[PDB]
Image (tube, rainbow, N blue to C red):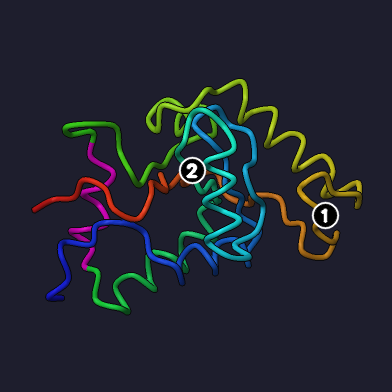
Amino acid sequence: MVEPGVAKLTTYASKQATDMGAIYVNSKGDRIVNESNVYTTFRNAILKQADKVAYLVMDERTWKKVYDLLILHDFTPEEIKSFFENKGKRPVFVKGSLESAAEQAGIVVDELVQTVKNYQGYVQDGHDHDFGRDPKYLHQFEGETFYIIEQRLEHHHHHH
Protein backbone atom coordinates (compact mmCIF):
# COMPACT_ATOMS: atom_id res chain seq x y z
CA MET A 1 0.00 0.00 0.00
CA VAL A 2 3.11 2.31 0.46
CA GLU A 3 3.60 2.12 -3.40
CA PRO A 4 3.48 5.49 -5.45
CA GLY A 5 -0.31 5.36 -6.19
CA VAL A 6 -0.20 2.31 -8.56
CA ALA A 7 -3.55 2.88 -10.42
CA LYS A 8 -3.44 0.23 -13.20
CA LEU A 9 -4.91 -3.27 -13.76
CA THR A 10 -2.09 -5.55 -12.50
CA THR A 11 -0.46 -8.68 -14.03
CA TYR A 12 -2.52 -11.57 -12.43
CA ALA A 13 -5.85 -10.03 -13.63
CA SER A 14 -4.67 -9.69 -17.29
CA LYS A 15 -3.19 -13.27 -17.12
CA GLN A 16 -6.48 -14.88 -15.89
CA ALA A 17 -8.24 -12.77 -18.58
CA THR A 18 -6.25 -14.23 -21.56
CA ASP A 19 -6.54 -17.60 -19.73
CA MET A 20 -10.34 -17.19 -20.14
CA GLY A 21 -9.92 -16.13 -23.83
CA ALA A 22 -9.59 -12.28 -23.68
CA ILE A 23 -7.46 -10.31 -26.23
CA TYR A 24 -5.30 -7.14 -26.26
CA VAL A 25 -6.14 -4.62 -29.05
CA ASN A 26 -4.74 -1.12 -29.89
CA SER A 27 -6.66 2.25 -29.88
CA LYS A 28 -7.78 1.38 -33.46
CA GLY A 29 -9.09 -2.10 -32.51
CA ASP A 30 -6.65 -4.60 -34.15
CA ARG A 31 -5.30 -7.39 -31.87
CA ILE A 32 -1.69 -6.41 -30.88
CA VAL A 33 -1.19 -9.69 -28.95
CA ASN A 34 -3.67 -12.50 -28.13
CA GLU A 35 -1.89 -13.95 -25.08
CA SER A 36 -0.14 -12.53 -21.99
CA ASN A 37 3.06 -14.53 -22.82
CA VAL A 38 5.40 -11.84 -21.48
CA TYR A 39 5.23 -8.00 -20.97
CA THR A 40 8.09 -7.61 -23.54
CA THR A 41 6.09 -9.11 -26.51
CA PHE A 42 3.03 -7.14 -25.28
CA ARG A 43 4.99 -3.81 -25.00
CA ASN A 44 6.63 -4.19 -28.48
CA ALA A 45 3.11 -5.00 -29.83
CA ILE A 46 2.06 -1.56 -28.45
CA LEU A 47 5.27 0.07 -29.89
CA LYS A 48 4.79 -1.63 -33.35
CA GLN A 49 1.89 0.73 -34.24
CA ALA A 50 1.58 4.56 -34.09
CA ASP A 51 -1.33 4.62 -31.56
CA LYS A 52 0.70 3.24 -28.60
CA VAL A 53 -1.85 2.03 -26.02
CA ALA A 54 -3.46 -1.40 -25.41
CA TYR A 55 -7.08 -2.31 -24.56
CA LEU A 56 -7.73 -5.72 -22.93
CA VAL A 57 -11.17 -6.60 -24.41
CA MET A 58 -12.93 -9.30 -22.31
CA ASP A 59 -16.47 -10.54 -21.55
CA GLU A 60 -18.30 -10.17 -18.18
CA ARG A 61 -17.67 -13.87 -17.16
CA THR A 62 -13.95 -12.96 -17.36
CA TRP A 63 -14.62 -9.82 -15.24
CA LYS A 64 -16.29 -11.95 -12.46
CA LYS A 65 -12.73 -13.29 -11.85
CA VAL A 66 -10.80 -9.98 -12.51
CA TYR A 67 -12.97 -7.77 -10.17
CA ASP A 68 -12.86 -10.50 -7.45
CA LEU A 69 -9.03 -10.92 -7.64
CA LEU A 70 -8.59 -7.13 -7.23
CA ILE A 71 -10.62 -6.98 -3.93
CA LEU A 72 -8.86 -10.29 -2.90
CA HIS A 73 -5.47 -8.43 -3.17
CA ASP A 74 -7.23 -5.47 -1.37
CA PHE A 75 -7.92 -3.18 -4.36
CA THR A 76 -11.27 -1.84 -3.04
CA PRO A 77 -14.62 -1.63 -5.13
CA GLU A 78 -14.28 2.20 -4.86
CA GLU A 79 -10.94 2.08 -6.82
CA ILE A 80 -12.36 -0.23 -9.50
CA LYS A 81 -15.68 1.70 -10.09
CA SER A 82 -13.72 5.03 -10.22
CA PHE A 83 -11.96 3.89 -13.45
CA PHE A 84 -15.49 3.57 -15.02
CA GLU A 85 -15.91 7.36 -14.47
CA ASN A 86 -15.22 9.68 -17.48
CA LYS A 87 -13.30 12.35 -15.44
CA GLY A 88 -10.22 14.22 -16.75
CA LYS A 89 -10.00 11.74 -19.64
CA ARG A 90 -11.93 8.62 -20.92
CA PRO A 91 -12.73 5.61 -18.51
CA VAL A 92 -9.79 3.17 -17.92
CA PHE A 93 -12.14 0.32 -16.87
CA VAL A 94 -14.97 0.39 -19.49
CA LYS A 95 -18.20 -1.71 -19.81
CA GLY A 96 -21.35 -1.93 -21.96
CA SER A 97 -22.29 -3.45 -25.34
CA LEU A 98 -19.48 -4.07 -27.94
CA GLU A 99 -20.00 -0.71 -29.75
CA SER A 100 -20.96 1.10 -26.47
CA ALA A 101 -17.72 0.06 -24.70
CA ALA A 102 -15.83 1.11 -27.88
CA GLU A 103 -17.31 4.66 -27.68
CA GLN A 104 -16.54 5.06 -23.94
CA ALA A 105 -12.94 3.71 -24.30
CA GLY A 106 -12.62 5.88 -27.46
CA ILE A 107 -11.47 2.97 -29.70
CA VAL A 108 -12.43 2.87 -33.45
CA VAL A 109 -15.68 0.82 -33.35
CA ASP A 110 -15.40 -0.53 -36.95
CA GLU A 111 -11.82 -1.82 -36.38
CA LEU A 112 -12.69 -3.81 -33.15
CA VAL A 113 -16.07 -5.01 -34.62
CA GLN A 114 -13.96 -6.62 -37.37
CA THR A 115 -11.53 -7.99 -34.80
CA VAL A 116 -14.39 -9.58 -32.68
CA LYS A 117 -16.27 -11.08 -35.74
CA ASN A 118 -12.87 -12.38 -37.04
CA TYR A 119 -12.14 -13.82 -33.58
CA GLN A 120 -15.57 -15.39 -32.86
CA GLY A 121 -15.68 -16.56 -36.54
CA TYR A 122 -12.32 -18.44 -36.54
CA VAL A 123 -12.84 -19.85 -32.98
CA GLN A 124 -15.89 -21.94 -34.09
CA ASP A 125 -13.97 -22.60 -37.41
CA GLY A 126 -11.10 -24.15 -35.33
CA HIS A 127 -8.35 -22.35 -37.36
CA ASP A 128 -6.94 -19.29 -35.51
CA HIS A 129 -5.52 -16.02 -36.99
CA ASP A 130 -4.23 -14.59 -33.63
CA PHE A 131 -0.45 -15.31 -33.66
CA GLY A 132 -0.98 -19.15 -33.62
CA ARG A 133 -3.30 -19.99 -30.69
CA ASP A 134 -4.76 -23.58 -30.53
CA PRO A 135 -8.66 -24.07 -31.08
CA LYS A 136 -9.03 -25.41 -27.46
CA TYR A 137 -7.65 -22.05 -26.04
CA LEU A 138 -9.86 -20.08 -28.51
CA HIS A 139 -12.99 -18.84 -26.57
CA GLN A 140 -15.73 -16.42 -27.85
CA PHE A 141 -16.56 -13.52 -25.47
CA GLU A 142 -19.61 -14.93 -23.59
CA GLY A 143 -21.75 -12.29 -21.83
CA GLU A 144 -23.98 -9.31 -22.84
CA THR A 145 -21.32 -6.94 -21.41
CA PHE A 146 -17.82 -6.33 -22.93
CA TYR A 147 -15.26 -4.98 -20.39
CA ILE A 148 -12.52 -3.00 -22.19
CA ILE A 149 -9.57 -2.28 -19.84
CA GLU A 150 -7.22 0.46 -21.08
CA GLN A 151 -3.68 -0.90 -20.60
CA ARG A 152 -1.30 2.09 -20.69
CA LEU A 153 2.50 1.76 -20.10
CA GLU A 154 4.05 1.12 -16.62
CA HIS A 155 4.62 4.74 -15.52
CA HIS A 156 1.59 7.05 -16.25
CA HIS A 157 -0.88 9.49 -14.57
CA HIS A 158 -2.73 8.20 -11.47
CA HIS A 159 -4.94 9.62 -8.67
CA HIS A 160 -2.36 11.21 -6.24
Mark 1 closeness class: few <14, some 14–19, many ≥20 residues within 10 Å? few
Residue 152 percent location from the top left of the image:
38, 46
Q: Main secondary structure of the magenta part?
A: helix
Could you tell me which residue is drawn at 62 percent across and 43 percent down? 32
Q: Is residue 13 left or right of residue 121?
A: left
At horizontal 59% and vertical 45% (from top left) the residue drawn is 45
Q: Is residue 77 magenta?
A: yes
Determine which residue is flagged by label 1. 132
> Which quadrant holds residue 61?
bottom right
- Residue nearest the viewer, comparing 81 with 13: 13
Magenta region: which residues? Answer: 76-85
Q: Residues at badges 1 and 2 in contact (C-beta under 8 Å)?
A: no
Q: Which of disc 2 and disc 1 is earlier in sequence?
A: 2
What is the number of the mark on residue 55?
2
Instruction: Give the answer, above or below, for where 10 lies relative to 153.
Output: below
The quadrant holding residue 79 is bottom left
- Residue type at mark 2 is Tyr
In the rendered view, does 106 fall on the left or right side of 135? left
Q: Name the secondary structure under disc 2.
A: strand
Residue at point 40%, 44% (across, down): 150
Q: Residue 68, position in %: x, y?
A: 38, 71
Q: Residue 67 sits in which quadrant?
A: bottom left
For the view shown, which residue lies furthest in the left direction? 160
On screen, 9 above or below 59?
below
Tell me the CA gap for discs 1 and 2.
20 Å
Q: Is residue 118 left or right of residue 150?
A: right
